[PDB]
Length: 341
Ligand code: NI
Image 1 (cartoon, rainbow, N blue to C red):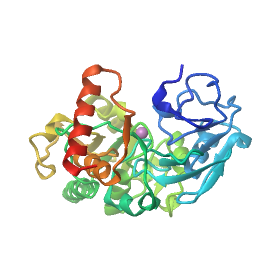
Image 2 (tube, protein in one colour):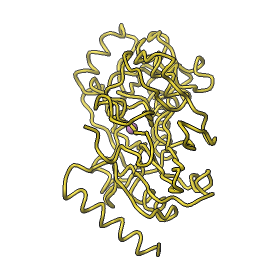
Image 3 (cartoon, helix red, strand yellow):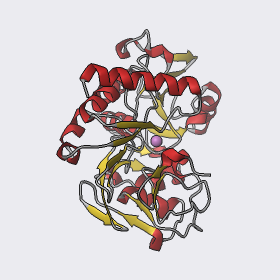
Image 4 (tube, protein in one colour):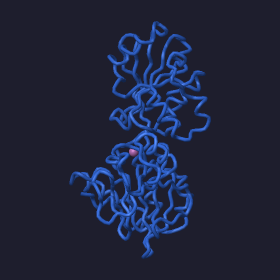
């Protein structure tokens, strides 16, 4: 049974609610982004209308085989009518194709559903600027002040500089980057660009990347591993055993691996600056955990909410425990008292 925080009152609509069977009263299922916790339940046998971005619709058709007649892609930043209700899709600054959804209810209420997002001051100049929002359905993944991490640009600067230094010292070093979903493509693309290489990967991953409308992608990635000095592997393989095993397969072309695990936040963030990050090493293998986030920091979240000034907040993450819920409600009230709304 579908939980309340996935239902949009006053409409026939649900958000990210595909794992509950046929939801009573739902005439249109929105999908914010192509991450498995959110698409859970979708398949080629789905026969209701799914509304989403173009990129998400490429992935539904090619990876999950949803039939084309049920996929309804909408352009961003454009007022659209769906089943009698005005909606807008906004870039969520999450993974490729991820959106926030603005719903303009028939009774005059305006609802923003962030999906998963990384708040940014650039959102203060989208179509959000033009009117009041009554209810905010908020990605609260990192809603606690201990959650600090650097900008995505500082993280990429560290990775490029690290990779270019290592391979220039040793031209026989291979770079490996872990992945288990879409998002964080800038990590492996920026490293391959500095090294003058394409990124090598499995056929299944190449297919996924080909759905993402990235400019000049055919110039950047390949399935020919032998021709590439930046390889992508499943995240589960980014450990000393998996990397040893991979180095064997490269036929003595390489004698060292430098690997990257983009994580979200890890508690090494409470003490250490990005500049000061060091790897775990065993022999000729080094592994860096880098804090590349596609969710808001606590401070970025707070800034967005204090600018938006919603009348009510409904969290969509960390909702399963009473301690979590009570923590989040306390920060919402601080924020509102501090800013005066
Ligand atoms: Ni996500």
